[PDB]
Image: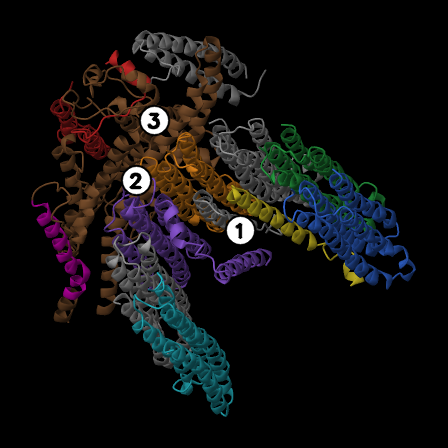
Chain colours: A purple, C red, F brown, G yellow, H cyan, I orange, K green, L blue
């Protein structure tokens, strides 16, 4: 558990330091020196937008990709005694790509809204640009993570489908209903991301 | 001040990609080879 | 200078006749069905592929963004 | 040298590719003395159309030199595969 | 006027609601699907009864959608911040609560399928327990809906 | 008249497909996915052209298309020597067996590369490039712009009154040297991939009607084919029509705030019809947008549940697990409706791979052979020798082999998943007659 | 002046280097001698 | 007269109360359902009694709903900050305390349900201990209600 | 007029696109080589076929090279920041996408090599599953390309 | 006029390229050497062929040396910062890419070398795969060379 | 004109060059020594040949010693910072590169010596592999020297 | 005119040198004593010679004492900071280098002493290897003495 111990030690020290610094700023009655509004305003909306775009596409493929090999290994292993599996159980992978597609479409549609500002001093500049920037960030994150977890779900379910079908061909069709729910969960994230960027403007 | 816009934004992107690197490296390190081969 | 009407007529007739009349002018061997399939499938896919390429470039919204050296060269090339 | 007839044959094919493609490149510039417009121009490019004609001739010369080297390479590889 | 960045928190709320509810549904769904497939190999006659846990998971996913949509439609540029904080709370409230519920959905459905696999009479009991998980998802949704209207 | 399997001698027969020296390879890549249902429509006669075409779009490279054919010809020229010999190398045998497939794939790749006018990133100048009249550019208040040009590019305006006219054949070569080819040509290929993908799907569906006739299943068209094709036409064919309309309806005169087909398509599905702020493609479009989506929904009940519903009606009157049949049909409906949306995305591989290849060709040329050129005569000539040799090596290693293989697989994917799944369904048995196979032994 | 620069540099430079030492020490601390050959008899 | 962002603390309170309580009830429910499913296979007649730990868990969930709603009703824009700290404290107090109680509810039910099947005389002892877990949950509710009105 | 540091984000994009893609392709290569070495002993005739997962991984590495070079050739000093973030997004997008692709390649290939040797009918399925992962990696490339003109 | 401390990034590049490349080669060398020691005791005639992984590992190390030196010779005091960002990108690009290749070398070397003793027909297959890892390392060098002079 | 704190970096370099290389050499020494002890019980006749990895380990430690001294003899209070960064990079380059080599030395020594105990023909192959580790160590030294004199 | 708290760094040096040196010697001592205790049961006649690893390990703590005091002898209030950095670097150099040596001593002592009883001919090889670890520790001292006096 050498790596888990490293991850934990970093995690604990990271937040423990934040607690000490935060409380100290309070204790020493600093003039709101740690100003969240300052961080949000100085941080260029361009980063937030491009980050959300990269997340929307990058997280979604990670999900799909995760599930693909989950079900790939189960299919390949079981298929040694039940080669019929490849005929029908490949649809589990189609669902996995489909989860990536949901995010991919949004990633492009969102990025199509990215524009320059020709802006400098945030003071009274880009009021709408900050809203659109944060919204695009959220919408990208929304769909990215939603597809990420969907892809894992579909992989786990598809694995059971392959193992089941190897022993009873009648089970395949009924199980398909579970993966459909998995796909629907990802679509829900798409609906929200669409709404979040439904009324935005850049530039 | 302790941080500038530049420094902070740089740290934010650095950590995001550092997490990606960590994820990749994690699974790469946790990679084993075979103890023995099945047959001749 | 060119119009679009003429390119369309020339290549539409070419591929159209092949896909429509072509099957009438085919060997009678055992591969006749394959050759007829080839003639028709080829004409349709090839025509549509080309047609988009030439049609899509009509009524353009913008021209190319060229490097300085090329822009000058064209003055005395085209 | 033998070098292996399988590798001599590969050299012959590359040599033929070289001579054919390099001569073609020189011709295209010589005729359109052009869309590619890659003769290795200077950055300080002046209003002198003759500079494009001159550089294009330079490209043809350089290309034919490269072809000449492929002619020598193909000749050598030819004898190797024939003797092997 | 309406300060900048005020919409930031409301966006995080709308995103959090959907993502955490998706997490809950995904866990409960994957766990339920695992148990169902394992049972159906041994006896397929219980498959239809064993489906409900999967819908139960989907409910958490919807819960999250309802609030995330409510907020996402409410999001604008000129937000008075107070409204954004209400949105932040509503988003987290339903998402994180649905996550807890979805976990319970997963664990209870998976164990429930194995239980019924051995003794079908457990069906009604297992559904009643999953009803408590649905109630936990509802409570989260209730609070989130209340906050968004303040 | 479609090709179907032969009769074999009231049990399910194996599927017998007669092939020859050329078509056998195509049948095998079909069989690799599965053995078709007895009396099923054989997809192979259409694969012979369809697959090379999809490759040619994925591999639309004029220069490599030639090299690809030459490789196939080499194998064919040794056909007699390879057949009457030992071939323990299975990879060589496989590509040999596919030698006639490869040749055709190259043939179409040349066709598509020629229209794209890309031969190792080289354009094909037919003396027809009249896109713009540079002499008039300077007249339009651009005097000595080549002085400032030292630090600028400057994009050639549309409709200045002096530009216009299409390129005689394919894309105007001038875009091959532009800095914004990446918007002009990328957009065209995007739209092309969508149009071709939708057409290919509609073709596959149309074939299902013939299969439904052959097996005398009127119900499979009354609640199947008809509502399914209505769904696809109303949504996906409409989109295609709009794409051509945009190209032919609007000129640069409306380039600012020009209607975006992506936004109108999204607003269509969502019934979002703003009064103003966004220009419409044509008057009344909002009414059409609403009409088509509603109709698409109206066809769904037939495809979703009426098939098992009428089967129950007819069954009980003649006298069938009604619940199970509802499950089957509901899943089928979801797969068809959702798959059409997903399948459309699948055909974006035509754009994605065509672009990816174009990026490899442009970059491999620019960062390898271009740098080998120099104003110094002898050094340039000798450098081109060594640099080109490496360049040709990279073109083979990266594009002719690896990418050609990738495009092979991706086009084959489209055939198996998106095309065949519209009509080529079910399974059959391997046809294994008595034959005198042991000739060498 | 420019505190944020020296601050940023020194903090993250010394932190990364300190961790490299900590991890290296961990890896050395827990070196596996094999616990075989003669160890089983001494154990 | 009041500072900005003062409402931030309050909304975190209302959310935290519900989320932690759902996490507590969810844990206890998940563990209880697992034990119930495993036990009831051997002793199906106990299915209608072994549900109780799950109800106990639902109580933790209500505890959270009550405070979260009570805080939500007290959320305004012109909050005096002082009141917001009290609301945050009330939210955390009941939520985190309910979380601890739900943990015990889970572990005690899991062991108790199986122990009861192997020992019917344990039923009374199991309930009594669960009563103690409910008392632990209430203590948090009591303080939270005191703070939210202070 | 150019915000300083504007070029910093851009340069990181070109690097990440190459590094993360190499990590993915290397992982897939390492996994495949392990399965290939174990399989090939008993069925050396399959050694040539077993390379395919590795070639596919190599494609992922190229995907990354294309973006890294495209960005590198697009770097200047007076970068307007807007362009820089587009390049950083392109790098990260293809990087993580290729990384995930490579992992799927490796994991599937390892199982595929063993499965095919035991059951040659699985050969096509092995290629198919790897093919879908390669298609997913392509998306990562394309989105990186799209951003270059936005 | 040039920003201060601008040399920091370029210097880190030169060192990073060398260190990460040594890490990659060191891993592949150590892992291959382990397989060599375990293998060649049974098949000493292969001792002069099983070194190849290790040689190819040295290539990764050179790739790093070439860039690390290229960067170091490119540094001055009055650096315009832009150039330094490029130097760090080039350093990391080749270093971390070589690191990824080093893992491939190590894993493939071990599996291949031991497999070769079991099946000598694997010898060529091992080289081909290791060749792919070397190609992956090359890509990093190419990009680093492009950036370092950009 | 000299930035204060500037000398801090150069001093850390001189230390790092020794500390990291010392960690590597120590690992290699301990790892090889363990294998040597195992060998000697089986057969002491090789005890004077298996020491080589340990002697080689020392060479790597010297690499670090040399640079650390060269940096220390190059430290001043009136440092121009540019030189300070070069010294930090040089120290890290040799230290971290020697560190990687040190681990490589230990791993291959242990495996080589243990194998040689059974197969004396392994000795020559062992030496070549150890030679590669020495080459990896040199590369770090070379760059560090180039930077420190830049 | 000197910076405030400039002694802070030099003081950390004097402490760090002693602490890390004790850490190294303690580790080697603990491991050496463990091997001695296990070994001497079989061959009590070696209990005396087997102490050497522990005696050698003490040399590390001595090294640390020497530098820690050497630094302390040079601690004043009016330190020019530069001198403080030198003291901190020297302290860390010898301390952490001694730590590396401590690991080597401990690991080699354990295996060596136990091996010696199994193979009396190992004694000389054990001493030689321990000598290399002592040389590695001295390198730290050498750098610290040169650096702290610069």
Q: Residues within 10 Å of mark 2 (few under 14, many from 20)?
A: some
Q: Which residue is the extreme one toward the right?
A: L45
Same chain check for tags 3 and 2: no
Spot occupied by residue A126 in the image (x, y as percentages of width and height) = 29, 45
Residue K105 in picture, x, y percent from top left: 70, 42
Please give left or right for residue F170 compared with residue L5 in the image.
Answer: left
Q: Which residues are magenta?
A: F284-310
Residue under pointer 1: B26
Q: Secondary structure at mark 3?
A: helix
| C-alpha distance separating marks 3 and 2 | 45 Å
Subunit of mark 1? B
- Reading the image, the residue beneath label 3 is F65
- Magenta: main secondary structure equals helix
Q: Nearer the viewer, mark 2 or mark 1?
A: 2
Q: Chain of mark 3?
A: F
- Residue F221 appears in the rendering: yes
Give me the residue at 23% from left, 65% from top.
F325
Residue B7 vs residue F282, the one in the foreground:
B7
Q: Residue at x 9, y 48 (%)?
A: F288
Q: Residues within 10 Å of mark 1 (few under 14, many from 20)?
A: few
The chain that hosts pointer 2 is A
Residue F409 in sight from this viewpoint: no
* Residue I129 picture location, percent across and down: 40, 48
Which mark is in front, 3 or 2? 2
Across and down, in percent, residue A89 comes to 36, 55
């Amino acid at each position: 558990t050498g790596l888990e111990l490293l991850y934990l030690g970093i995690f604990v020290a990271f937040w423990a330091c934040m607690i000490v610094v935060g409380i100290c700023y309070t204790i020493f009655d600093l003039g709101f020196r740690f100003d969240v509004a300052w961080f949000l305003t100085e941080t260029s909306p361009f980063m937030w937008s491009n980050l959300g775009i990269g997340l929307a596409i990058s997280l979604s493929v990670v999900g799909a990709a995760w599930g693909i090999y989950i079900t790939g290994s189960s299919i390949i292993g079981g298929g040694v005694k039940a080669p019929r599996i490849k005929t029908k159980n490949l649809v589990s992978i189609i669902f996995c790509e489909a989860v990536a597609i949901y995010g991919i479409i949004m990633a492009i549609v969102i990025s199509n809204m990215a524009e320059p500002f020709s802006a400098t001093d945030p003071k009274a500049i880009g009021h709408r640009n900050y809203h659109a920037g944060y919204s695009m960030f959220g919408a990208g994150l929304t769909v990215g993570l939603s597809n990420l977890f969907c892809g894992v779900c579909v992989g786990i379910v598809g694995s059971g489908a392959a193992l089941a079908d190897a022993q009873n061909p009648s089970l395949f069709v009924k199980i398909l209903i579970v993966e459909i729910f998995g796909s629907a969960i990802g679509l829900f994230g798409v609906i929200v991301a669409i709404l979040q960027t439904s009324r935005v403007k850049m530039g | 001040g302790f941080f500038s816009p530049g420094i902070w934004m740089g740290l934010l992107t650095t950590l995001f990609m550092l997490f990606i690197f960590t994820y990749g490296l994690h699974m790469i390190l946790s990679l084993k080879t075979m103890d023995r081969f099945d047959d001749r | 200078a060119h119009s679009f009407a003429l390119p369309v007529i020339i290549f539409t007739t070419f591929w159209g006749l092949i896909g429509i009349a072509g099957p009438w002018f085919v060997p009678k061997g055992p591969n006749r069905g394959v050759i007829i399939t080839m003639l028709v499938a080829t004409a349709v896919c090839c025509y549509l592929f080309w047609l988009i390429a030439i049609l899509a470039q009509l009524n353009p919204l913008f021209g190319p963004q060229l490097k300085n050296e090329t822009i000058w060269y064209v003055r005395f090339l085209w | 040298l033998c070098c292996g007839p399988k590798l001599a044959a590969c050299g012959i094919v590359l040599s033929a590719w070289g001579v054919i493609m390099l001569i073609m490149l020189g011709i295209f510039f010589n005729v359109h003395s052009l869309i590619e417009d890659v003769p290795f121009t200077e950055k300080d490019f002046e209003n002198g159309p003759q500079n494009i004609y001159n550089l294009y001739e330079q490209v043809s010369y350089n290309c034919f030199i490269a072809a000449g080297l492929y002619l020598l390479l193909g000749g050598f590889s030819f004898c190797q595969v024939r003797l092997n | 006027n309406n300060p900048e960045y005020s919409s930031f928190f409301g966006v995080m709320g709308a995103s959090s609601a959907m993502v955490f509810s998706a997490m809950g549904a995904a866990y409960g769904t994957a766990k339920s699907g695992t148990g169902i497939a394992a049972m159906s190999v041994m006896r397929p006659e219980l498959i239809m009864k064993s489906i409900i846990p999967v819908v139960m998971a989907g409910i958490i996913a919807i819960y999250g959608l309802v609030v995330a949509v409510l907020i996402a439609n409410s999001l604008t540029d000129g937000i008075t911040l107070y409204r954004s904080f209400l949105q932040l709370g509503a988003g987290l409230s339903v998402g994180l609560s649905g996550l807890a519920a979805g976990f319970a959905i997963g664990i209870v459905g998976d164990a429930g399928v194995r239980g019924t696999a051995q003794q079908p009479r457990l069906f009604v009991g297992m559904i009643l327990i999953l009803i408590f998980a649905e109630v936990l998802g509802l409570y989260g949704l209730i609070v989130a809906l209340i906050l968004s209207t303040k | 008249e479609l090709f179907r399997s032969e009769e074999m001698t009231n049990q399910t027969p194996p599927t017998y497909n007669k092939t020859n020296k050329f078509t056998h390879g195509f049948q095998n890549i079909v069989d690799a996915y599965g053995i078709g249902t007895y009396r099923e429509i054989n997809p192979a006669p259409y694969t012979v052209i369809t697959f090379p075409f999809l490759f040619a779009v994925m591999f639309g490279d004029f220069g490599h298309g030639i090299l690809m054919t030459l490789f196939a010809v080499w194998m064919v020229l040794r056909e007699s020597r390879i057949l009457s010999q030992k071939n323990e190398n299975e990879m060589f045998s496989m590509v040999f067996s596919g030698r006639y497939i490869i040749l055709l794939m190259g043939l179409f790749s040349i066709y598509t590369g020629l229209i794209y006018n890309d031969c190792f990133s080289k354009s094909l100048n037919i003396f027809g490039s009249s896109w713009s009249v540079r002499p008039m550019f300077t007249i339009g208040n651009w005097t000595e712009e080549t002085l400032l040009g030292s630090s600028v590019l400057q994009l050639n305006p549309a409709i200045p009154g002096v530009f216009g006219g299409p390129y005689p054949f394919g894309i105007d070569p001038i875009w091959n040297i532009a800095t914004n080819k990446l918007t002009f040509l990328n957009s065209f290929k995007m739209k092309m991939s969508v149009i071709l993908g939708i057409i290919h799907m509609l073709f596959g569906v149309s074939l299902s009607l013939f299969n439904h006739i052959y097996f005398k299943k009127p119900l499979n068209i009354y609640f199947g084919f008809i509502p399914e094709i209505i769904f696809m036409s109303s949504l996906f064919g409409y989109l295609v029509i709009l794409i051509f309309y945009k190209w032919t309806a609007y000129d640069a005169h409306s380039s600012r705030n020009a209607p975006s087909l992506l936004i109108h398509f999204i607003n269509m599905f969502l019934f979002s019809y703003p009064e103003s702020g966004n220009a419409m493609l044509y008057s009344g479009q909002k009414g059409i947008q609403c009409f088509l989506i509603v109709v698409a929904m109206l066809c769904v009940p037939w495809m979703l549940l009426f098939k098992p519903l009428i089967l129950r009606h007819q069954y009980l009157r003649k006298k069938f697990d009604f619940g199970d049949t509802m499950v089957h049909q509901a899943i089928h409906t979801i797969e068809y409706c959702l798959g059409c949306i997903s399948n459309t995305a699948s055909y974006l591989r035509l754009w994605a791979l065509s672009l990816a290849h174009a990026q490899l060709s442009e970059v491999l040329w620019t960062m390898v052979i271009h740098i080998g050129l120099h104003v110094r005569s002898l050094a340039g000539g000798l450098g081109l020798f060594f640099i080109f040799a490496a360049f040709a090596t990279l073109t083979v290693a990266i594009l002719l082999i690896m990418e050609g293989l990738s495009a092979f697989l991706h086009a084959l994917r489209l055939h198996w998943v998106e095309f065949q799944n519209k009509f080529y369904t079910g399974t059959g048995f391997k046809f294994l007659p008595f034959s005198f196979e042991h000739i060498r032994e | 002046l420019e505190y944020s620069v020296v601050f940023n540099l020194v903090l993250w430079i010394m932190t990364g280097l300190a961790l490299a030492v900590i991890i290296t020490s961990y890896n050395i601390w827990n070196m596996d001698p094999g616990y075989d050959s003669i160890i089983y008899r001494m154990t």
